[PDB]
Image 1: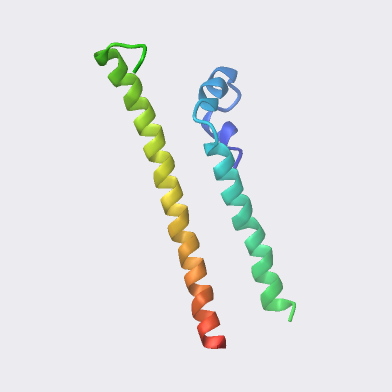
Image 2: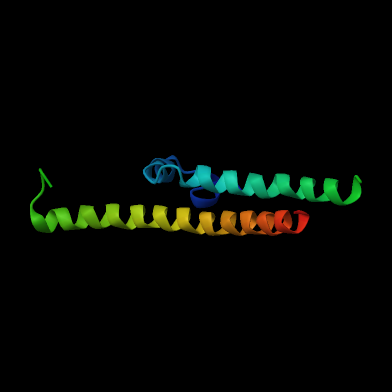
Length: 49
Length: 49
């Protein structure tokens, strides 16, 4: 998820307001990327034996 | 606290409280899920032992 496109969409005005909450969009994208890499790990360790 | 009188300050402080408390909740939730992952790995290591 692009946390900024989700929360604000195209708006620059919303994007500037959003930046004042700081790291939260980075935390969200980092969590979803970790979940995504775990799915390749899961398939690797089940099938690539 | 150096700069605004009490009733104007209280609104600004309530904004800081809200966002900081949400940052703490995010931390403690992610730590509870990491704790479950390490707990599972510790149970596996106890079995391996």
